[PDB]
Amino acid sequence: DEINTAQDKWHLLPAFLKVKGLVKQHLDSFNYFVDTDLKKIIKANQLILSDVDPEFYLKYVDIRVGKKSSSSTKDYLTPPHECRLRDMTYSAPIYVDIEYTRGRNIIMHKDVEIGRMPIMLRSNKCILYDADESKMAKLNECPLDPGGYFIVNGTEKVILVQEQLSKNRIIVEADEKKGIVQASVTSSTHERKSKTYVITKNGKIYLKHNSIAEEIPIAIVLKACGILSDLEIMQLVCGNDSSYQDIFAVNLEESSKLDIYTQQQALEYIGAKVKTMRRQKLTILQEGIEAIATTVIAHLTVEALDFREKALYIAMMTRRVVMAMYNPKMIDDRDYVGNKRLELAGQLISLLFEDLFKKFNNDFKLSIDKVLKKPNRAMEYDALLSINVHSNNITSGLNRAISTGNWSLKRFKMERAGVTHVLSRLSYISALGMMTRISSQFEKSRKVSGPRALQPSQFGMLCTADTPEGEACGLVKNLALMTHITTDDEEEPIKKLCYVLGVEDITLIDSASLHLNYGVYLNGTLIGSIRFPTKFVTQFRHLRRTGKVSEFISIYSNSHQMAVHIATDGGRICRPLIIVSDGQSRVKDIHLRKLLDGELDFDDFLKLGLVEYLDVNEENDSYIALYEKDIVPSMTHLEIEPFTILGAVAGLIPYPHHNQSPRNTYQCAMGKQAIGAIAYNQFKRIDTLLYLMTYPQQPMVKTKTIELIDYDKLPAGQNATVAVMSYSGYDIEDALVLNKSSIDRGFGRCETRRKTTTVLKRYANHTQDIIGGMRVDENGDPIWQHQSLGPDGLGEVGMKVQSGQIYINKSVPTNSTQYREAPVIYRGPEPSHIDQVMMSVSDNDQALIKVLLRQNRRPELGDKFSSRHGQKGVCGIIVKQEDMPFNDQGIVPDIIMNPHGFPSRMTVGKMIELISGKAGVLNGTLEYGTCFGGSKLEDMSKILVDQGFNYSGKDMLYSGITGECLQAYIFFGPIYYQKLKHMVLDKMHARARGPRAVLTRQPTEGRSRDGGLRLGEMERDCVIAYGASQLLLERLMISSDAFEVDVCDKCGLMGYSGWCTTCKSAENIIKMTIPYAAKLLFQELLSMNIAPRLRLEDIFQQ
Amino acid sequence: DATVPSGRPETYIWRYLPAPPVCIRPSVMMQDSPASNEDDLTVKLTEI
Amino acid sequence: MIVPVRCFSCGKVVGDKWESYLNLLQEDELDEGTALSRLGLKRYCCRRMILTHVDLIEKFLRYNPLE
Ligand SMILES: [Zn+2]
Ligand SMILES: [Zn+2]
């Protein structure tokens, strides 16, 4: 059969995912870091000098990670799974070449190790790089693991992708009853500042910088930037439009209102307002200080006597202000996807290593000064002993930042937290969706839903369904299936190209004609103007399609703001589109035939100009066809495959276009909590918590996404036989009816594995913990506490541990000779089985014991299930098989789900999944429920009819309890059901009395500590509304904190032992019961100078 | 109201500090170092 | 992991049909549907038992720690 371009252009998606994986943002970022950013940091901080001893220097020549020049092979790294087991860090050493001078004129190189680099999994420096599943089996790694995370001290940490507003770009925002402000958060390589730019009153425009004391009138700054005609100021910021002239003319008057101006006068004015520079170079406090004020006002550093570039930047800043003044809706949406950048793990680590290396260099030079301050016998030989010692700080800080997620950067001066998160191991999809997850910038005033709404501009860039619930709804975002994040490209090769293509530099343009023709902006900066912007843009796009410029550089034109924009910075989200030229697509299936046969990988589609990346901004200039059949002769691009607007996790849903969107979002939530298969080495893993399905099945109705992400290899769920009917009355409100004897045969059967870690730590007294024990009774048998403990004092593998038994018999020295018992005791309502005991040591030569406790779990009453469509519920009842309805063949549903869950939720995709799965099981073929596609319902009905079933999947069942025919036909077929990690066995809590917090003498706070349930303000209000005073007393004093205090009747002060200890008499002391909270509050008030004296009267005497 | 003692305004100037009872500011046992860990209020009153 | 002994819904023994199904697919190749029907898996529950099974025990055995 010949290739058809419409239904075979989707193979570009597997071709693209083959070389550009889902976890590729992290991988590319880390590879770029360790390959070039390390070099850049070493070259920037290349020479640390000393004030003393000028004939002496230290030069950083080269930097390398994990490889020396002694051999072609790399250094042996501890394998990542061994790092996970041994609670160490998967890291490679950093090497540098050092040019340190000798006292006798000797020049030499070296290969010096200055610390350890926490290596990303499956990066260029990783041992799992291009491993063929046999090397992976040998290294105890799942070949289906995403990689892209770090193992620091045995913990898998992922540096989440970060959203932020784009730097070095103008953002104009309006307001009601406040005025208009528009900012430019400008980040240089060493200083970040926000040149805020506000209007105060009378339509007067001011510039408001952090360094400047008071907002400067805009005419002052425009004159200070060399633009001093004061007619070209208004020509630059208003052009020929009469309205903007009137709006802006007020702050021309205030330019002369103070006094008329030269450039240098306004320079001195602006320089007067500079705040301080920590009192260094004080002799610059003149008109010269304004030069640094202007040069460090933005990212357009001026290194000459020409200020036209910054002057025009401020002029366009002002002009955007003035357009916003004339009308709102000329402001730009702050939640637009094109106005945001994605910073990645490599960038984070590059900046963190920059800070750590700066600290390392400063402390090394301090040590150098301390060594060389001695007068005599200053030998030079082996000046690197100190560097051998001082290499530990780089490793320590680099590990601690990733482990904690807190990033204390002194140079740039912000404290950000939550950078890294422990990788989710609930399920394979949980880990994969934790990768490709994006966190949005904080300080957002979450009270509004501004940055919470779905934007249309995220189409094909961010998944439209994979958003969390509860609190981070719309803030945590996920990458779409087929996306790319641009890298930084040097802009000076392409400014030259713009000049070649007809752009006239702003130094050749006059102010009067600037708003006559289009301007050309490079990364937000007006570099020049051009005639024929359409032709310029077309030429640039042709030059990019032919590979003369980077395919990630974006060019687009703006009609409202007369501007051609070119973006080369990294962090821009983009996706590939098929180029449509002259009303025809450019792929035409000869390329598809070559692609399928083996030639022409995805990159060659870019090299031949058949596909190109479009960021959110070029999509404004594009006109995309979703399909081939709607290619009209005005369209610029063609969708490769439209289901890629859903992410990896949302791709688990069959027929999501037939569902209500909240159901798809809820399934994105639930699939991450589904219990299934973790990895091919999941039984080699020793994790803190791990739920595993005993008999996972691949879904009968799958999608293209689940096979692209290999979810059918580690599926989390089972294809339950489902009868959609009301049954037994225990299935109202999402509750499910589960079949006993389907549970007996292993349906929904899972197990949980839990690790407990103990270290036998050495102490300064040369003492350490021990694991000796296993005391016996006189009959030889161990005591009950030690029934499963083994001779070594560590529980025996395979033995059951009941609650109260010891499986780690650790003894601690009493003078950390004599050992006090501190054994690890099993505290579980249900018994577990020791399935693994691992003895090892960590990198710091210290004993490490890990015990894996496994526990089989029968699906019981209250356990949660879901069905890939947001239809979750607990088991309401477990019924015998003979009580279940049966069909003519005797098929009995495993699960019965209420039909009442359908009409209001409108999960038609679930019904289509039932029919498609029934047709698939009867036909022997796994069906497809792909978004915007899948297996047609009519073909499934044809299969059903041809096999003797009703076309709509409704079968005549008999009642299992009466035996008669059910009067309605029942929707009967297979549905994929996921068992969720919320089992009632881990939720059932009950406290009568027990642990109390000593401070408040109230019950503890957690189910682990046997805490009580908090009767809060709302419950107290409900009880008050009932009028139950005695119940209020019983719940809030008698059963929470009832303290029998002694109160003196004379002075209302609390005593002890019936003694006033303020009146020292005990005659007026009486006895009453108050909350210990009241006692504590009175005593705390007495700690301040507040004496809440109690006044007492008799209850009786009427 | 100066009917009762301590109604004099001069008692409203910090002269005596009523150091709170131990139960008000508990000291935790075996925290991090084998040594007991004190708390913020005790540290502040030590410094005072 | 390993093929369940019995169909979850029916209780029919399907754990003795996994290998014969694999050999029906490999040796003298058959379609999956006709291979399932040739093994007596008539009801769709017993059909999905074999059709949807993921033989994860073979992948697990690649990490055998007692070599
Ligand atoms: Zn008293
Ligand atoms: Zn069956």
Image: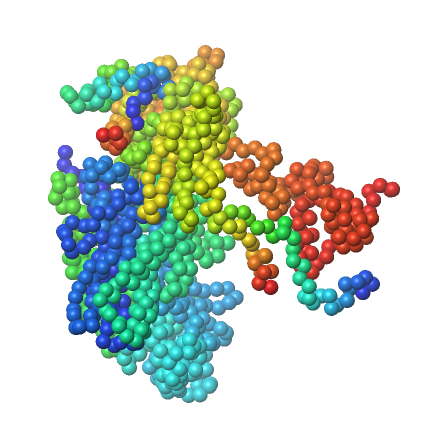
Q: Is residue A430 above or below residue A24?
A: above
Asked whether A273 or A552 is in front, the reply is A273
- The spot of residue A293 in percent (x, y) is 38, 77
For the view shown, which residue lies furthest in the right direction? A1101
Q: Is residue A704 above or below residue A495?
A: above
- The spot of residue A137 in percent (x, y) is 23, 36
Asked whether A947 or A1097 is in front, the reply is A1097
Quarter the C terminus of chain A occupies: top right
For the view shown, which residue lies furthest in the front direction? A817
| Side of A1005 where A493 appears, left or right | left
- The spot of residue A779 in percent (x, y) is 46, 20
Q: Is residue A981 above or below residue A477?
A: above
Asked whether A601 or A74 is in front, the reply is A74
Q: Residue at x 66, y 47 (%)?
A: A1077
Q: Can residue A875 be seen?
A: no
Q: Residue at x 12, y 39 (%)?
A: A597
Q: Residue at x 39, y 68 (%)?
A: A193
| Side of A778 where A914 appears, left or right | left
Q: Is residue A733 above or below residue C44?
A: below
- The spot of residue B30 in percent (x, y) is 51, 47
Quarter the N terminus of chain A occupies: top left
Q: How many numbered marks are there?
A: 0
Q: Residue at x 40, y 19 (%)?
A: A744
Q: Can residue A393 be seen?
A: yes
| Side of A1083 where A591 appears, left or right | left
